[PDB]
Length: 285
Ligand SMILES: CC(=O)N[C@@H]1[C@@H](O)[C@H](O[C@@H]2O[C@H](CO)[C@@H](O[C@@H]3O[C@H](CO)[C@@H](O)[C@H](O)[C@H]3NC(C)=O)[C@H](O)[C@H]2NC(C)=O)[C@@H](CO)O[C@H]1O
Ligand SMILES: CC(=O)N[C@@H]1[C@@H](O)[C@H](O[C@@H]2O[C@H](CO)[C@@H](O[C@@H]3O[C@H](CO)[C@@H](O)[C@H](O)[C@H]3NC(C)=O)[C@H](O)[C@H]2NC(C)=O)[C@@H](CO)O[C@H]1O
Ligand SMILES: [Cl-]
Ligand code: NA
Ligand SMILES: [Zn+2]
Image 1 (cartoon, rainbow, N blue to C red):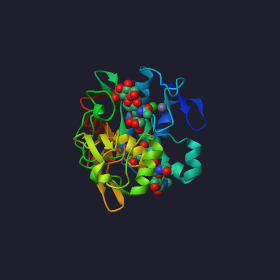
Image 2: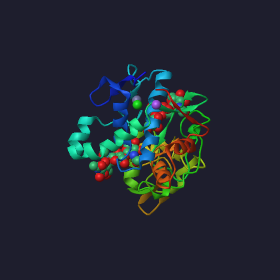
Image 3: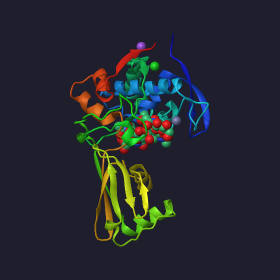
Image 4: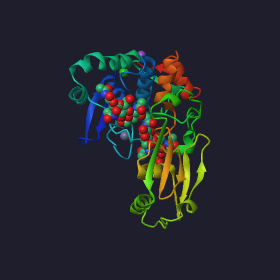
């Protein structure tokens, strides 16, 4: 049969809209990747995005949006940019010359999903790793045979591979106190009170001690708007520097990694089987 119609929760308007898969995936790709990425990277992303929807259909309904399979918020499911949005933001020439490449990538992989033992997988993906992807359980909760840590040697060419942020000691404690009212921390000798308790081999900070509090790397990323939870802290006179690696949760497929592999000659099946361990590709329509 033809492309299914899905229920998408638009987090901005607050309404559930019906959309055709293909048209929806064009919007996902437009927001997740640049039209300037290699066709093989875009194709890999389109398969993951499609697989994400299929995976959610087969599993339990979400707490956030129970009437919708996926939503338009990259913080919950994946990014989305409608045709009108992109038209007003980029123009008619862009739609005809660049967006066309996105549509071609989506139709290029029509009905294709990533599978583990013939079922659709949870195809998590993110911008840039630190050099290795993360095992699902070390970042989230559960262990999956296909979300394992693998090398990602082209990530170092990403503009988002490294970043640093300086925060005064004062603002460091002020931000923590505003977010955690029970925190007992002193602006002097932060180096004696702040320390990383547990970190994965890939580098995601799982636990970090701040005074009397134990937070996760994600918690820190959130409070200070860092690109990732893979960071180290260096204490200076009057400030702290966060030295961050990568951008995004680090599990599954690296978008800049895929771009790097594609630039080196790899095709979308090999990109997808490299990041999603022991998987295959299946055409469901
Ligand atoms: C394409 C992509 O990677 N999108 C990202 C989202 O997947 C991600 O949402 C978070 O996803 C993980 C994995 O699905 C969720 O973890 C699950 O949490 C539940 C309950 O807490 C637990 O039962 C599951 O075992 C656990 N899954 C795993 C694999 O361990 C997590 O709850 C989602 N977070 C939120 C806030 O909804 C978001 C946010 O990280 O980013 C997208 O880019
Ligand atoms: C006309 C034109 O293309 N102008 C450029 C903009 O497209 C560009 O916007 C940014 O594009 C990138 C895609 O490479 C977006 O990155 C993605 O962001 C989402 C979260 O929204 C995240 O899930 C993805 O991991 C991430 N992808 C990658 C590969 O890192 C980024 O959000 C876009 N920002 C926007 C739309 O505000 C800007 C960026 O400066 O440059 C124009 O020249
Ligand atoms: Cl499709
Ligand atoms: Na197909
Ligand atoms: Zn969602």
